[PDB]
Image (spheres, helix red, strand yellow):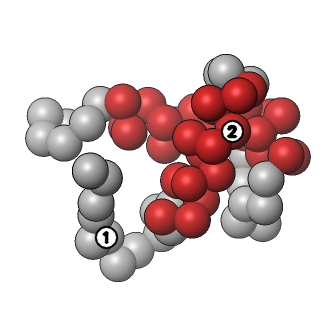
């Protein structure tokens, strides 16, 4: 289970696919993921780490 409904500048469910798809092999290698999978133009590798952070901060509390 993994759902959401934010109609604003955030990751699509497609980018979050590649996020975990990457980390599941890569481990925490963020620049590597950013290059390995198709992601939003003008991204930084931090955006991956930063979204991931909120993903592992789960629902509620934040």
Category of crowding for the residue at label 1, using alpha-carbon neighbours closer than 10 angstroms: few (below 14), some (14–19), many (at least 20): few
Q: Write down the residue under mark 2.
A: 22
Who's the residue at 19% across and 42% down the image?
59
Residue 44 left/right relative to 3: right
Who's the residue at 69% across and 39% down the image?
22
Category of crowding for the residue at label 2, using alpha-carbon neighbours closer than 10 angstroms: few (below 14), some (14–19), many (at least 20): some
Who's the residue at 31% across and 70% down the image?
6
The numbered mark at residue 60 is none
The quadrant the C terminus occupies is top left
Residue 1 left/right relative to 34: left
Residue 44 visible in the displayed image: yes
Q: Quadrant of residue 61?
A: top left
Viewer-side label of 2, 1: 2
Who's the residue at 27% across and 71% down the image?
5
Percent x, y for residue 8? 40, 74
Q: Write down the residue under mark 1.
A: 6
Residue 34, placed above or below residue 53: below
Residue 15, placed above or below residue 44: below
Percent x, y for residue 3? 28, 60
Helix, strand or loop under label 2: helix
Helix, strand or loop under label 1: loop
Residue 47 visible in the displayed image: no
Mark 2 or 1, nearer chain start: 1
Percent x, y for residue 15? 59, 59
Residue 48, placed above or below residue 13: above
Q: Quadrant of residue 58?
A: top left
């Amino acid at each position: 289970g993994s759902s959401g409904s934010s109609g604003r500048k955030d990751f699509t469910k497609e980018e979050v696919n590649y996020l975990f798809h990457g980390v599941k092999t890569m481990g925490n290698h963020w620049n590597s993921i950013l290059w390995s999978f198709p992601f939003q133009k003008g991204r930084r590798a931090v955006d991956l780490a930063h979204k991931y952070h909120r993903l592992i901060s789960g629902p509620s509390s934040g």
